Image (tube, rainbow, N blue to C red; front, side):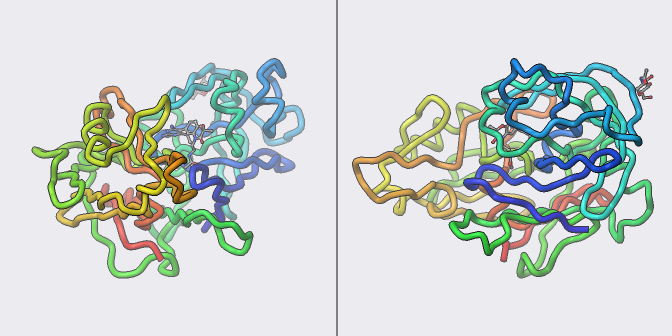
Length: 333
Ligand SMILES: CCc1nc(N)nc(N)c1-c1ccc2c(c1)N(CCNC(C)=O)C(=O)C(C)(C)O2
Ligand SMILES: *[C@@H]1O[C@H](CO)[C@@H](O)[C@H](O)[C@H]1NC(C)=O
């Protein structure tokens, strides 16, 4: 099954899922970086403006709802949400599964007031699941209906017209229509996390980073490519970028000429061009242009680690192989 995704400003990719009976619709991000499912709850106080602006699941309207109530808190690198567990049936592109999810009652204005999506569907392993809740993909696998024990991601480049699909997730395989050439796999450092060994990072013709090796979390839920603060400072220094509060800018007229950035993964160099990582919104030297690469210190046990997000997947179609505990990459088409 494939799920059509909407692309919002190249930073948000989300699709629809149905919860309850009758189905209550929600826009959600499919996140390989987390392992829980959650949507805003009707029990979320309207004092949380984010709840006033998103779809709210109302258990009292679903006949398939099963109460639980265990509280849980989900912590992401850029924000936190809190609530309680509930069980109901969920629709994901034709597949139906009974799933335990979180009803969020505390949704911070910053950053959720900036979210086009309502919730999140974690595609990670149960090892990282908060409350030890069985992840949705595991429940799907349990049905023995998927052709293959894998899921893939396609994140299109932003578009000014509504004729192009923002992206696409495939449960059970990959869509040959959105990649070309062959997949090149890398084994997961360890099952339980969509993280792989990265052999090196280069800026221009000089592998000046991640020498001696480092970690790379392949995170479909992250908007950008991130690295430790030290790594980024070094990388950004080589680009001549200026560190801002939340990001890094560069004189727009300078954007088109920034050097290539490569990521050495499993014996293959994955190269991004300035066009691939800078939001080229102008060529003016009197304006600043943001880079789709940020600094982010991911704490243990998962980090320190670099994170390959939308900026990376936009260029390389990505297959997540559960059965073989490896990740596949192929040039996106
Ligand atoms: C999708 C959940 C999520 N998972 C992971 N692994 N890391 C995160 N930083 C986030 C996370 C949290 C809050 C967010 C966003 C992401 N995102 C990006 C969502 N990612 C995609 C690919 O759409 C946002 O835009 C704002 C609103 C800041 O709020
Ligand atoms: C919630 O689900 C977990 C999973 O087994 C269970 O242990 C717990 O008792 C449930 N909570 C309630 C009271 O429904």
